[PDB]
Image 1 (cartoon, rainbow, N blue to C red):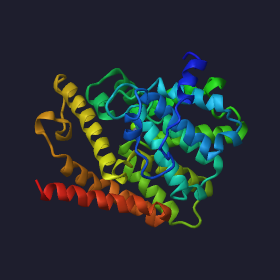
Image 2: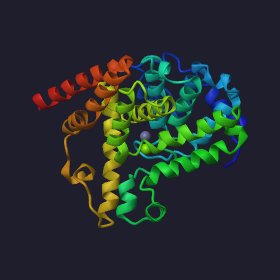
Image 3: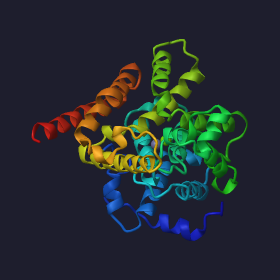
Image 4: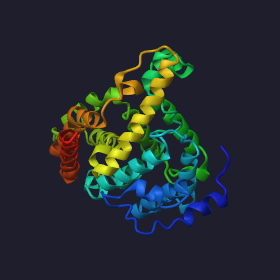
Length: 333
Ligand SMILES: [Mg+2]
Ligand SMILES: [Zn+2]
């Protein structure tokens, strides 16, 4: 892992993002990517602007140069895949910013925990290859065998944590270097707990633990804070359907193409190909989006807003608007 050069930093620093408010719930990362021929630089500049605008790095002795080094060390470890690329983790970072500051979830957390969530967003899918946990287990790939042998089925989430620790192990990219003792431990533990909680196999149990803690006025304070962090990174990771309909749609097309490529590899490998991953089933976007809204996203966002996070009401409102827009697509087909 080479040091970040001055030249790589300079190429981010020249990006000015004219006409973009990176803090707005209607910010459009696709419009931002279309706005220049250096979209990776614009993406990095968005993450940089969000982290500095929070005012958090400054307070924890993270310099502007170490912050930018961290962002470019994260960027180098994302792959050219259609969905789980740098644009996704920048999107999750921007979305968490909106939940924290537009949704007032910052009131539930310390400044350190807010800083950790914004940083965690950028590490949470490091070196994703566009294949899910199931692909590794079904194909008995080396990484799959290692996960089974060691007793952790979160194949990708554990691998993502390993590369986060590797980045933070150099002071030149350690955004937590200004911390020590209990604060530094909490930074690393909560980052790792949050990334491990993004495994969708734990979705139901993560959501039930958070709601049981939110409903309990005698909940352990440290445990409530940790579960709030976990739920906010999960919220960010499944936020595509909370965005304006055309943003929501371009994300769903990116997901679908990634799923199709996995199904192509499962096919040429003779393993089970779910319908969702099958090119030749030509399954309807509108039906997929409504299915995901009805069974996963609307109940998740409705329950966390009602339990505790009232300031995130807009997420529930937009999912409702997006579900009616998809119903109009079906109605007019
Ligand atoms: Mg992930
Ligand atoms: Zn993700």
